Amino acid sequence: QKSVLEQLKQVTMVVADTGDFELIKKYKPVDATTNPSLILKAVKEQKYSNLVAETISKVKANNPDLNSDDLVKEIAIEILVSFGIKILDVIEGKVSSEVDARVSFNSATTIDYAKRIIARYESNGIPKDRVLIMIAATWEGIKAAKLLQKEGINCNLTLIFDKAQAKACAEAGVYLVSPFVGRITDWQMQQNNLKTFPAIADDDGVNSVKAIYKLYKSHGFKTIVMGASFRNVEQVIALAGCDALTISPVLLEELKNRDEHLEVKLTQISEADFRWLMNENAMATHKLAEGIRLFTKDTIELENIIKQNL
Ligand SMILES: O=C(CO)[C@@H](O)[C@H](O)[C@H](O)COP(=O)(O)O
């Protein structure tokens, strides 16, 4: 009698959503993802302070020409990479590293940031095939990802809240999309001051991923659909069969400790078109923007921590 976690792995690529590599080992996910909030958490909790201190010393040594601001930016990238490297030691698949959320509306600076991350991984002996560059799915992010994919850099288009938005990502040939589930359900609950989670059939977040999956499979899009942002284990279970699901260590532990039967449930857009379709979706418009704001705040806090340790 396999746990729900082991049953899930039979039909879905399980991915760990964390920067805490020591936790990853015990769940044996295929891939791992680290957003700016998770990098911040890992750095703040100080489980890896030596790794951080060493990263700061290394970057200073190799960059005697950089001023304070430029140096901090280079250290921030090296920290993302350092965590990714430690994760890659304990998984067989890929790790996702996110570009600075502040470049979300600039395709050119997104491209350059993505390339810098990739170059730092390569300088450290990690080939680009083991990495996904995570980019917020604004029109600018998708356009950047289109170019990056053409140049062999696989991308993880995140902060996906609308089906049309997911369709445009697939049209750009992106490797993977991360449709959010929990934040969509959060909007749904706040709309009507719901205190309890909706029934699964009525969960807007779960339904959004189901609709994206259905679209991708019927249209033959090869982009991987990876559900992300979970509020509870029931939302993860509801998406069993999805191509991939990125899950927090807490929820992975919950899945590992449950042993009931797991029902397997899942088995040409122009810029103007894209902007129109996103505008029609109040939730998506708000949540994409909020996501970028929140990740920005966490990136700024990480910068502040770096600055205090120079
Ligand atoms: O999409 C990814 C990685 O592909 C995750 O890192 C999400 O950023 C995370 O799952 C959001 O979770 P909440 O912040 O909504 O709890």
Image (cartoon, rainbow, N blue to C red):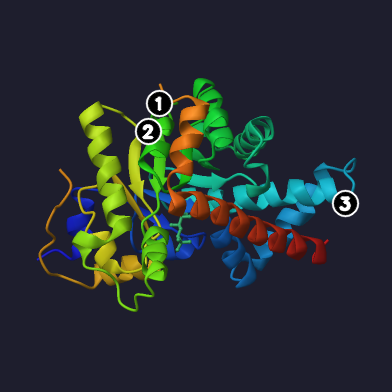
- The N terminus, quarter of image: bottom left
Q: Residue at x 21, y 67 (%)?
A: 199
Q: Amino acid at mark 2?
A: Lys
* Circle 3 crowding by C-alpha within 10 Å: few under 14, some 14–19, many from 20: few
Q: Amino acid at mark 3?
A: Ser
The span from disc 2 to disc 3 (Cα, nearest Å) is 41 Å
User: On the picture, is 70 further left or further right than 84?
Assistant: right
Say whether disc 3 or disc 1 marks the residue closer to the N-terminus.
Answer: 3
Q: Are marks 2 and 1 in contact (CB under 8 Å)?
A: yes
Residue 287, how many percent across, how many down? 50, 55
- Look at the picture and state if 228 lies above or below 175: below
Q: Residue at x 54, y 34 (%)?
A: 139
Secondary structure beneath label 2: helix
Pick the residue in front: 146 or 89. Answer: 146
Q: Which residue is mark 1?
A: 171
Quarter of the rendered image showing ligand 1: bottom left
Say whether disc 2 or disc 3 marks the residue closer to the N-terminus.
Answer: 3
Residue 109, how many percent across, how many down? 69, 34
In the rendered structure, find residue 273 and report the number of the disc placed on it. Answer: none
Q: Amino acid at mark 1?
A: Glu
Q: Which residue is mark 2?
A: 167
Residue 22, how many percent across, how many down? 47, 64
Q: Are marks 2 and 3 in contact (CB under 8 Å)?
A: no
Q: Which of the two discs, 2 and 3, sits closer to the camera? A: 2
Residue 64, how many percent across, how many down? 89, 43
- The C terminus, quarter of image: bottom right
Q: Are marks 3 and 1 in contact (CB under 8 Å)?
A: no
Q: Which residue is mark 3?
A: 68
The span from disc 3 to disc 1 (Cα, nearest Å) is 40 Å
